[PDB]
Image (spheres, rainbow, N blue to C red):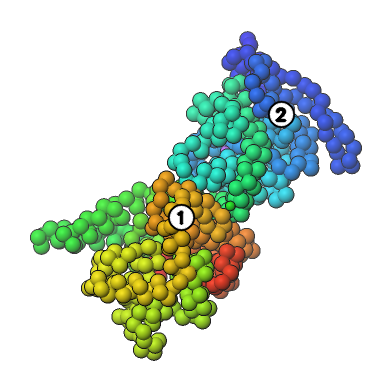
Amino acid sequence: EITKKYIKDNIINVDDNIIKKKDIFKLKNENNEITECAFEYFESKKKFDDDIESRFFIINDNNYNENINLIYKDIKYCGLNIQTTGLEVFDENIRLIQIAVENYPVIIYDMFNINKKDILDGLRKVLENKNIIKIIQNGKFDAKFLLHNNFKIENIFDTYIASKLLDKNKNMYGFKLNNIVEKYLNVILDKQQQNSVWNNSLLNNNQLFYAARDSSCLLKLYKKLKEEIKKENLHIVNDIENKCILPICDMELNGIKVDLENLQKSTNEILNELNIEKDNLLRNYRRLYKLYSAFYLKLPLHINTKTNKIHTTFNQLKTFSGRFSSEKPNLQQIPRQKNIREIFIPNDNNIFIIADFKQIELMIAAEITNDEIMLKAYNNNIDLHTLTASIITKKNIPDINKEDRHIAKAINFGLIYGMNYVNLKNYANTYYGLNMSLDQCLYFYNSFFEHYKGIYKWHNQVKQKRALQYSTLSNRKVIFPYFSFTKALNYPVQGTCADILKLALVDLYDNLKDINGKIILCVHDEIIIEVNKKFQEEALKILVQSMENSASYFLKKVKCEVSVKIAENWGS
Ligand SMILES: [Cl-]
Ligand SMILES: [Cl-]
Ligand code: NA
């Protein structure tokens, strides 16, 4: 009886809190005349002990009144959330789409009980309207579901990204919605309802009050977190990261197509190999054993049988440095040999363009340290390993040879990141195959820091201060648990690289729309895009200019170097 009171709206009154009510709301038509309209909404009987908007409109095919769309007139921002039947976008559907507009009940789109397009026209206009801020928690997740269900969205403020940046990698956990709301608003949402079955055709009264509340809280969170972001001078990094959601979604949705012929043929090749090595019976066996078991055995599990592609998961802020991380599969863990890389290929009538930054870590070090010899050397287009070779050997560039440059690579990568001369001996002889003496390495140390005075000043200022707070050129921030000299030198370089790559993906995303380019992959200091073969030379220019513009945003005293190649596979 009471349970059956609002089946008309596909709701179940399990308890006795849900009450339907009708009242007039304050609204305005296009002619700047106050049309105050009547609407039917739902409110709890037991009042919540907080100011979070718990009331809501529910939209369905039955009780659709067009005038709720006019709530969106002249808004500047709105809370946005969805409720899904699961996590995997391809294998799941959006159950609810909630829109929280300030000082009104939460508008909830019942997607399982709407089969007409005209209702969603109001929603689609809001989401496309670049002049509305969409406050979201877990913006990549929601944006993926919307983009896959043909919705379009621009202009996002992700409370997860804001909460992570403000945390400065002091915590691994505590970035769920209930955690963030408990922290910044001191409110405990009903986190049981995250697990509750949204695949039901009807929904219970507690589910929808959770639905509404978990969107309306975003308005208060937006005020608190935007203020906190501005206090900590994190607006530049937070703004880049929010804009970077959409390129990330483009990568996770586009995926990368796989050549199953060379994959299976290659897998049979490794079979014949390791069986033949057992017949011949550490070097070749563990090579084949890991190459098979790590690569050729696990990669078949990730490809989608229908589409012949891998859709990896890109993490945005789950690293110390701030660089992207990838998992399921970890794209950086793919072997760098060409025989395997060539398996990954474009789609039909498309082609890869692949661009790498060159020496960007060293250039960033020159920038931030103001090292005169390095900066003027880069401006003259003199290679830094050639430069160090000249300083060490005291020879001129026409006399420097490949052996000198090799020792110089060990000296630069060794000493720039904080190694002493003993660690330089072990580092060079291990990773570069030299046999340097400790007297020679001591000469390299004194000569290197005698000439590179900015780098020397950088190292001694860090070692003297023993600080824990460190930052990048985007003002991304980290707080160390304890002082580590090498980590302290590594953070501004690597974190500025992450800033450059992420902003490059933002500009690249906005620029590739005309040719309908697809962003595929970002690993280390490399970016891969797909375009139809007619836009080949064009997309070459778009990619290089986007990456250069990002590096030009952050770096003033040094011009980056992009190496770009067009390819029909990753291994080229
Ligand atoms: Cl600051
Ligand atoms: Cl901001
Ligand atoms: Na969400």
Residue 105 image label: 2
- Considering the numbered disc 2 on the image, is that residue within a helix, a strand or a loop? loop
Q: Residue furthest front?
A: 464
Viewer can see residue 335: yes
Nearer-the-camera pick, 391 or 64: 391
Determine the residue positioned at 59% across, 22% down: 206
In the image, residue 148 lies at what x, y percent? 56, 46
Seen from the viewer's position, the closer of residues 224 and 93 is: 224
Q: Amino acid at mark 1?
A: Lys
Q: What residue do we see at 56% from left, 67% from top?
A: 555
* Residue 429 position within the rendered picture, expressed as x and y whole percent measured from the top left: 25, 69
In front of the other: label 1 or label 2? 1
Asked if 553 appears above or below 292 in the picture, the reply is below
Q: Residue at x 54, y 38 (%)?
A: 93
Q: Quadrant of the N terminus?
A: top right
Ligand number 3: quarter of image: top right
